[PDB]
Image (spheres, rainbow, N blue to C red):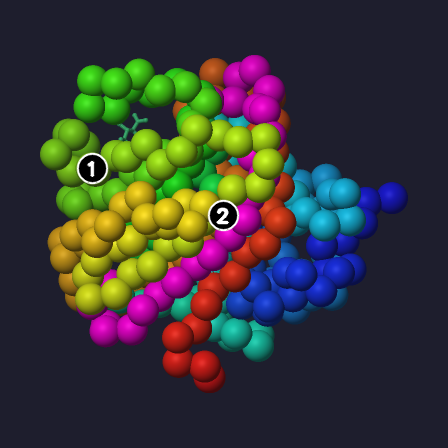
Amino acid sequence: FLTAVSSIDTFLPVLNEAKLQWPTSALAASSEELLGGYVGSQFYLQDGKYMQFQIAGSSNRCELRQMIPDGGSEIGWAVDDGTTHTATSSIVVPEQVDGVEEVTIMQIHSGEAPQLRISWIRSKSLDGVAYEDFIMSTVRIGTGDSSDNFVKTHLADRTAGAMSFQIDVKDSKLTITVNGNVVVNGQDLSFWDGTDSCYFKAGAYNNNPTSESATARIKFAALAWVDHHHH
Ligand SMILES: O=C(O)[C@H]1O[C@@H](O[C@H]2[C@H](O)[C@H](O)[C@@H](O)O[C@@H]2C(=O)O)[C@@H](O)[C@@H](O)[C@@H]1O
Ligand SMILES: O=C(O)[C@H]1O[C@@H](O[C@H]2[C@H](O)[C@H](O)[C@H](O)O[C@H]2C(=O)O)[C@@H](O)[C@@H](O)[C@@H]1O
């Protein structure tokens, strides 16, 4: 039988502040249901320690979406509200099966757009350099489709072992720290000033696969939204 993520203590804080969306953005499990032992092949405890997400299909997901804590509704915050918004994780990205090409593992998203995607990607060239099997950040600085709307950065080559991430937003600036080192230092998010619908996400969101039956799989050793105001 499949062991439930809530059977250990590690993820209870974030489960109390998230809903699970699967296999689309449709609700799969409320925060209460997650804390109550919701489990399936898409979302279960692997190795007695990892919150594991699995999903197949282009643009499908198995993803946590930040909620107001203690049974609250969907959160919305703004890059320019003056508060520091922080998400931390420790992630084991396994080798992905053929047909999986890009898997978004953390986001800042709003009602209409992804401000930030951290994604594993099989192969991509950035600024004239080819990279394989790596973790990328994609920041939107506009809503258009041309390259001037994005800042894309190689964060790290994929490691077999756990990799730590931290996302911080304060005063319209974004910092991404990977394995303790700052890789994105104060990226401008001021295009999004006044958008009050931002929230964190984490899990597996499957982008541009070449087979819709190929199952993406991501293991979280830790995940939290860190509240700088201590409510
Ligand atoms: O053609 C691309 O791969 C294009 O995708 C962009 O990311 C999109 C994702 O693939 C998903 O469709 C979803 O998350 O929307 C994203 C978006 O529209 O921002 C960027 O990665 C872009 O650089 C790239 O050209
Ligand atoms: O699937 C999408 O295109 C986006 O869905 C978003 O979730 C919202 C959506 O209205 C859902 O049907 C449900 O109501 O939850 C909403 C929400 O939590 O904001 C996000 O999952 C977004 O990341 C997707 O891009």
Callout 1: CB less than 8 Å from ligand 1? yes
> Amino acid type of disc 1?
Phe
First in sequence, mark 1 or 2: give its number: 1
Please tell me whether residue 82 belongs to the stretch shown in magenta: yes
Q: Which residues are magenta?
A: 79-101
Q: Secondary structure at mark 1?
A: strand
Q: Is 70 situated left or right of 176 in this image?
A: right
Q: Main secondary structure of the magenta part?
A: loop
Q: Position of residue 210 (x, y in %)?
A: 48, 16
Give the alpha-carbon distance from disc 1 to disc 2, as whole Å. Answer: 24 Å
Question: Which quadrant: the N terminus?
Answer: top right
> Which residue is label 2 attached to?
164
Up the image or down, 106 lies above or below 192; here it is above
> Amino acid type of disc 2?
Ser
Q: Which label is found at residue 129?
A: none
Q: Is 166 situated left or right of 42 in this image?
A: left
Q: Is 90 situated left or right of 113 in this image?
A: right
Disc 1, disc 2: CB below 8 Å? Answer: no
Q: Position of residue 125 (x, y in %)?
A: 28, 19
| Residue occupying image coordinates x 20% and y 18% | 128
| Residue occupying image coordinates x 55% and y 60% | 19
Q: Position of residue 25 (x, y in %)?
A: 49, 48
View quadrant of ligand 1? top left
Image-quadrant location for residue 53: top right
Up the image or down, 192 lies above or below 25; here it is below
